[PDB]
């Protein structure tokens, strides 16, 4: 699935745009 900025072993596009990982 797609960006859990609420799971924090982020997918890592999801990371950089959680603002993050």
Image: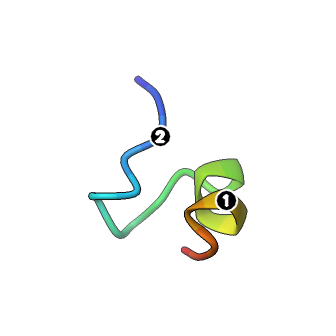
Residue 20 position (above or below residue 16): below
Quarter of the rendering occupied by the N terminus = top left
In x, y percent, where is residue 19?
Answer: 63, 72
The residue that disc 1 covers is 17
Q: Nearer the viewer, residue 20 or 9?
A: 20
Say which of 17 and 10 sits in front: 17
Circle 1 crowding by C-alpha within 10 Å: few under 14, some 14–19, many from 20: few
Rate crowding at label 2 as few (under 14), some (14 to 19) or many (20 or more) other CA atoms within 10 Å: some
Q: Quadrant of residue 18?
A: bottom right
Residue at 67% over, 59% down: 17
**Residue at image mark 2:** 3
Residue found at the very far left of the displayed protein: 6
The image quadrant where one finds the C terminus is bottom right
Residue 11 in percent (x, y) is at 54, 51
Residue at image location 28% in from the left, 58% down from the top: 6
Q: Which mark is residue 6?
A: none
Among the two numbered marks 1 and 2 on one chain, the one whose residue lies closer to the N terminus: 2
- Residue farthest toward the bottom in the current orientation of the protein: 20
Tell me the SS state at disc 2: loop
Instruction: Please state which of residues 9 and 5 is positioned toward the viewer in this rendering.
Output: 5
């Amino acid at each position: 699935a797609l960006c859990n900025c609420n799971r924090i072993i982020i997918p890592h596009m999801c990371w950089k745009k959680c603002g993050k990982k």
